[PDB]
Image (cartoon, rainbow over the protein chains, first blue to last red):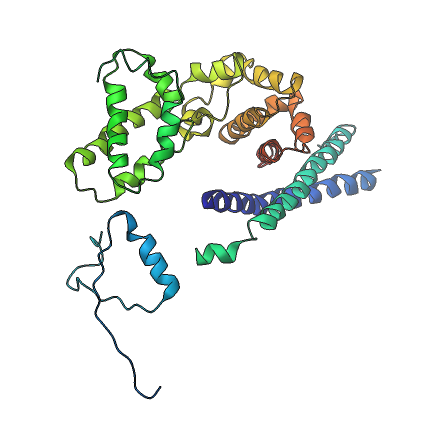
Length: 41
Length: 47
Length: 49
Length: 212
């Protein structure tokens, strides 16, 4: 019963501390495709 | 209550099967002091 | 991309990828909080037991 | 003791009720024969149908995981201290034997294969990194084939565990599911009512996109 709770919040939290970084790298990629398009036009 | 108490040194005979459950019922009562029968033993091999 | 009309494919590629990356971050949070809706319950008996 | 009686009593619920007495083990002589009877049940059986007494006995019950802490205790009888090492070389061999590519192929081709230790084992996914490639991508195209046409009230989570573990160990496998449209499949099935299939589909789509 406890190894489910131990391995869930160990897998999810290290996913969350990695998938936030993969998300916060991508939103600053989505804006610099948006910003340089109007800047080129 | 102006004197202290009256003790016993009673000796338990707990079997193999009822060695967890009797001490568990001794834990809910809580008027029992266990004496270390084996002092000269290391921190392991204690069964 | 250095070219026109390939950044249009790129900016709509990051547009759908962020949507699939935000739909998992909203789903893992209320799943992790659904763990602590049940596993954070009965912790005090589990310390006592 | 006679091998002809082993396959005669197997038409019963013999081992799962015998595992339900092994978890109590209060008298310490009740389980001391049950560990010995299981060795007598398997070794005195000259056939290859002990794999039926693998798929019923220990991979579907909480008795394989119970052999370790029965070894870690300090048992006094010398016939039980040799019985725990005899069943581990037996059952250790059985876990190893259980994981094989052909068996997995049957599981997703003959189908209806459940939450057996063929999916849960890391030793399964350790070796067959290119087995999903070696079937000309059709092995990646028949697991998802059963995921999309059928409702699968229980086994839908099992193949979602198959794709989530495979894209963790092989980074190029994510491009296969991107052309296949199975990424849209796990985004739909994660909203399902059953918490066993909702979590594993949630576990799959968080493993498809680990690095982008």
